[PDB]
């Protein structure tokens, strides 16, 4: 295929918040109620130690009499979110040793903004990218966005390959979820339903460069080679997982069924992934535990579910646990943060069998329910 | 390249709104004011006779004490817009002689909805498309979306060509703008600014099937072959055109510069398009007047601007005027409606000098400002 990730960059925002950040804001704006009690309790059962945020509980946006409107949310997405995407993209470009003029496409995603021009326009502008740049801003897909953007970039790379053209694609995910805290609080208080969104999600931008190899001076270094991918939708599961537009932003839909449906989808999707490319793999990469696993940490039960279904230890998904515990679920931006972390020396120390694996399965689930899986070779 | 459009389908909603529709609603919900007076005057000089709509001025969505919220807008996008998209897609597939299992990708666009799962998920499910379908839902681009989606589908088709696989891509645009009438009325009244969007925009869904030829019969019919494409961003023009998310939907941004910038972009974009394919065109197809022009009718001065810049008659853009006069500006869905109409016998009889052209230039502009242009060969 000639497809390789030649750079990765991750930018988390300045603030790191413990579980009491939610308690502070809840107390400030709502009297205690049964549903709030339940959710405040759940906020402490996730296994997330700290979450990344563009701000703290005293930020003016979330301290109005009302939750901020979707317009007010957009304003902060641009002032505090966009800067993170530019820095993540610069880092990925620096690692890949590419200059702005060499970027041929950009595939971006977010589920926590709506805008025309889209946020990718402003990022490309700050990076000084070409006025001829081909851009894709994906919408509709939430947490599976990082891998869906990577898969989309792969297809686009191969389109240029078919024409004998160099392709260097900036693949970007930016999520700013923590600003919707007051919206979720209002829904919990007024509707008295146990909405677990406030407990899970955080802010982040992450980027990789995907190259089709054409035009590279030979023997050029890469971090991962992209070998293959699979994608599926789980039937009759639209009502289980979603993010509905609202004058207050977007409202989380997240049912108890989600981690059950996700776990059941793992084994047959992995089978299809592996069968499409097994003849490219060595004898030491045959069963799920032989690989390192870059799982999107959608929640604690996704990780324990995956360990259970595939027969893995936590250390097989060490970088996933690392991001989840220390940063929380940053939706589409999390997966590239995981792949970035996985190749660092202190994750190497924790490799199952004392063997850092040459092959990595990536996996993510999102609204649909959409399942995304990919196979990487780590150089 | 082996790329062709093998089917097209267009579905307008049943209702047609004359210039009185805006008068009815404004009088019902707002006092007389200078800004309202100006907009009501301008409305009658747009060059539009009728605008296609999912409803009439007595629709309950637009007759509440306040404008509908973006949540209420989504509900109607889903109930009234999605069925148009399913039917436009069905018709494109029918002309292409394809069954649901043959569709390998879907590339969709809208700027008048935000949802997760996006509207494309629900359209694909209604059509019975594959659980393995690769989907792209574009955001951030508004009116240029039809051609951006076509261009994106072109790169994706070629991705499959690189692997020797068949690609048949459903390319879909759906816009429902008429529902934001109370939002724009409120802005005109409140801000006392002459906002002309209310007078221009309408509702439509349109779709094409783009094929990469692999596994097609030798010399398989098509309606158009896709020969090439160009895309550019006009620098320093983000403020000139846009669609900002808001509790009441999205608010139109439009400066006086737009017609001049659009007009001025034609010559260099066209020159680049043609330079990239000079020895694929006959010498009888060199200057703009040599081609038929499928121009996105953004407004009357866009069509007249193009005539002036490029030395064309109104009949060079006959299908563009036909859509504009009779249906209004349906944003991203308009271009495929124009391309569908252009090939009808009725438009043939109005060709410049009675010469129906073998090559068609498609052109659209949207927020960015993004310019898109493509070269089609008509069969
Ligand atoms: C800026 C001030 C910081 C305030 C305290 C920080 C705590 C914030 C709680 C997080 C709110 C979560 C809102 C849910 C976002 C959902 C993301 C997409 C999920 C999906 O794809 O369905």
Image (spheres, coloured by chain):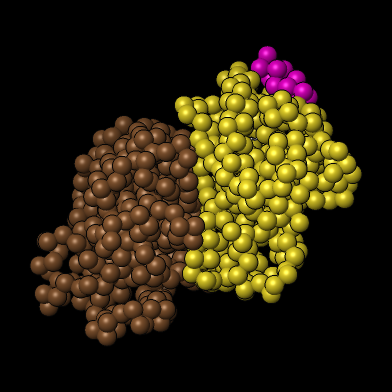
Chain colours: A yellow, B brown
Q: Is residue A33 magenta?
A: yes
Query: What residue range appears in magenta?
Result: A31-45
Q: Position of residue B39 (x, y in %)?
A: 32, 56
Q: Position of residue B45 (x, y in %)?
A: 24, 62
Q: As drawn, is B180 to the left or to the right of A308?
A: left
Tell which quarter ligand 1 is in. Answer: top right
Q: Residue at x 75, y 65 (%)?
A: A221
Q: Is residue B203 above or below residue B339?
A: above
For the stretch drawn in magenta, what is the main secondary structure? helix
B80 or B361, which is in the foreground? B361
Q: As drawn, is B297 to the left or to the right of A308?
A: left
Q: Is residue A195 above or below residue A139?
A: above
Q: Residue at x 70, y 36 (%)?
A: A287
Q: How many marks?
A: 0
Quarter of the image with the N terminus of chain A is bottom right
B29 or B378, which is in the foreground? B378
Quarter of the image with the C terminus of chain A is bottom right
Picture quadrant where residue B300 is located: bottom left
Q: Residue at x 79, y 28 (%)?
A: A47
Q: Position of residue B130 (x, y in %)?
A: 42, 38
Q: As drawn, is A305 to the left or to the right of A73?
A: right
Residue A249 showing in the rendered view: no
Q: Is residue A179 above or below residue B10?
A: above
Q: Is residue B1 magenta?
A: no
């Amino acid at each position: 295929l000639g497809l390789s990730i030649t750079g990765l960059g991750v930018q988390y925002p300045p603030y790191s918040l413990g579980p009491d950040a939610i308690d502070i804001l809840s107390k400030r704006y709502h009297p205690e109620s049964p549903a709030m009690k339940k959710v405040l309790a759940i906020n402490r059962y996730t296994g997330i130690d700290q979450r990344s945020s563009i701000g703290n509980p005293d930020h003016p946006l979330v301290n109005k009499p009302n939750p901020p409107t979707v317009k007010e949310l957009h304003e902060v997405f641009m002032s505090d979110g966009v800067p993170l995407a530019v820095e993540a993209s610069r880092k990925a470009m620096a690692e890949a040793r590419l200059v702005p003029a060499q970027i041929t496409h950009m595939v971006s995603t977010t589920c926590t903004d709506s805008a025309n021009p889209g946020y990718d326009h402003y990022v490309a502008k700050e990076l000084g990218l070409s006025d001829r740049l081909e851009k894709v801003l994906l919408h509709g897909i939430g947490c599976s966005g990082g891998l869906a953007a990577l898969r989309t970039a792969a297809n686009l790379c191969l389109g240029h390959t078919a024409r004998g053209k160099p392709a260097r694609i900036l693949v970007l995910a930016l999520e700013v979820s923590t600003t919707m805290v007051r919206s979720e609080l209002e829904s919990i208080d007024a509707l008295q339903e146990t909405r677990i969104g406030i407990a899970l999600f955080s802010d982040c931008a992450s980027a990789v460069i995907l190259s089709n190899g054409i035009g590279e001076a030979p023997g050029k270094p890469a971090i991962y080679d992209l070998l293959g991918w699979e994608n599926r939708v789980i039937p009759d599961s639209e009502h289980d997982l979603g993010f509905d537009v609202d004058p207050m932003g977007w409202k989380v839909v997240l049912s108890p069924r989600v981690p059950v449906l996700a776990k059941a989808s793992l084994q047959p999707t992995y089978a299809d992934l592996l069968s499409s490319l097994q003849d490219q793999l060595p004898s030491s990469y045959q069963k799920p535990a032989d690989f390192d696993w870059a799982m999107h940490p959608g929640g604690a039960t996704i990780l324990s579910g995956a360990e259970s279904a595939m027969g893995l230890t936590p250390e097989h998904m060490r970088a996933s646990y690392d991001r989840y515990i220390n940063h929380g679920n940053s939706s589409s931006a999390t997966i590239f943060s995981v792949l970035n972390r996985l190749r660092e020396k202190d994750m190497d120390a924790l490799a199952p069998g004392g063997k850092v694996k040459e092959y990595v399965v990536g996996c993510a689930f999102g609204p649909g329910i959409n399942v995304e899986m990919c196979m990487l070779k780590r150089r």
